[PDB]
Length: 196
Length: 196
Image (cartoon, rainbow over all chains, first blue to last red; front, side, top):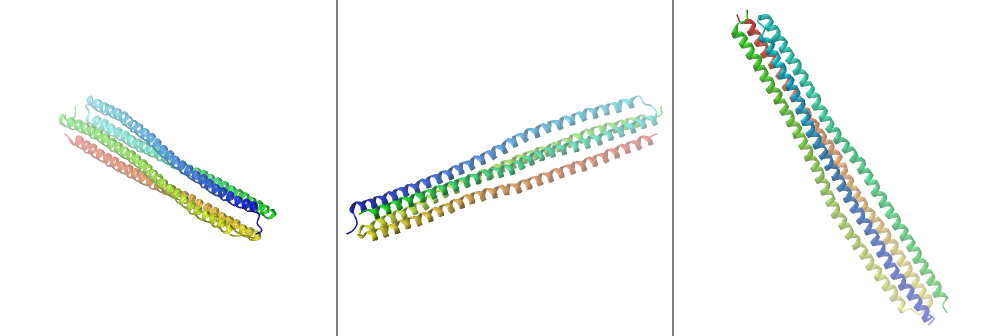
């Protein structure tokens, strides 16, 4: 029987050592991979929370703006009502001392036209103001939407880069592991063949 | 003095009635406008809350998927580890009864190559599987983003339509109010002029 006992022992120790090494490498890689997925999932949840925070803040800001706009509308109406009340008062007072029919009608004609001129201006102003408010709110909302488009792009780019880094590192590690295993097997085969 | 007392009274009653009418119309319009802005602001806050709900639900769903993917990876690794342990066992057993040097080396060569072939297949599978998981998650996220783009479009269209309806209704109301005021003033002027 032409196999030296110590040589057989050496070959068996190398096979056993290789088994343990390979098992450890497989577990190590599984752990590193699992960790990366865990981190990626937690990072994605953090980003969802940030997006929600951004929407809540914007809604809070929109709430304040709308309330202030309502007050400003109330104030604008109140100024117009003060002016209107003054005109009603002066319209009537002026007629109190007028005693010629034609003059009374002429002053009435002026009062009527004045009231219509101011009504037209007040109505038009309010349409212009309400529209501006509407446009401001739509513009704020759109800016928030646009920013979410680019943020989502950036978030997806970052995630794909981390994934790529992870897959490249795993591949380099697997490759080096294979090289080492083959070199250890190759050395053991030389040694076995050389043994007397 | 050529103004009939009752005619003067009638003219003054018409001017006073017009003042009250106009004041009531201005307040009425301000109330309707304020109401519309209030409703629009509450509707916008409801939509912000809905967007947040959608993000929370999606994050919850992504959480479940990632946990299941982790378990599936664990299971896939465990199957590969069972196979690897069986191969280590059979590799060694087979050598136990081999007593010719060349045969022992030849079987060792086969064991080494088998282990490398399976390692290569297990590594490649894991890279393919991890990538698919990564792609699935990126695809879910992108679909959610895409849906938010179109939802934001729909929400903005609905709001602009309601704003347009509101501004058109206010304008029709103001126009009718002006027509009525002018007709009442015109009738009063006829009556005053006709009075003896």
